[PDB]
Length: 137
RNA sequence: AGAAUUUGGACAAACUUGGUCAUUUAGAGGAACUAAAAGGGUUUCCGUAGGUGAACCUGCGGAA
Image (cartoon, rainbow, N blue to C red; front, top):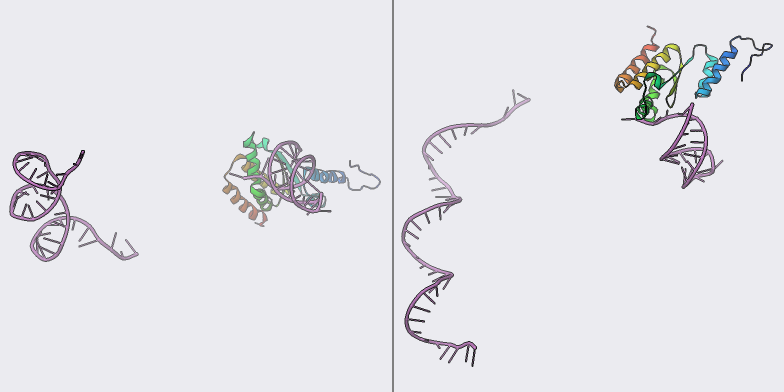
């Protein structure tokens, strides 16, 4: 429970930022990863399910979670580093933390992994988006 | 019962020898044909068995 103290609280948004902090820890993000929300003002969490992308069931759903994660989490590790985001893959529930354009690119990468795009095309696209994001022009 | 041994009649192994058939092979010539080679189950927890400072790790079964 969080409550605004009018005699002490001064920022009108503090309640929402504190609540958005608390949810990030709830969703599964590490604490130091959750502190970025309080510290920064342009970090957004993107949340969605595998079923939203495609109605997969049984082993088809399990393979989809595998394709997103990859062996030893390599594919998930690559997506977070290329897009400069933080991803929590809780079964079929995905939570992506980062900047707007950043999580927009991570979302496309995850969806392509769900829908079955070839691994090479995803990895190659991860190379390009990694560089293109950091460039001034 | 077998005889040693003898006369004569057939069966007949094996050997020498002149032929005639079939099969291999030796050199030496004659002549014909062909060939020839540089460059896809991660994260946080729960239960259990084992190890284990039951800290922690591994196997299995569950939840987000």
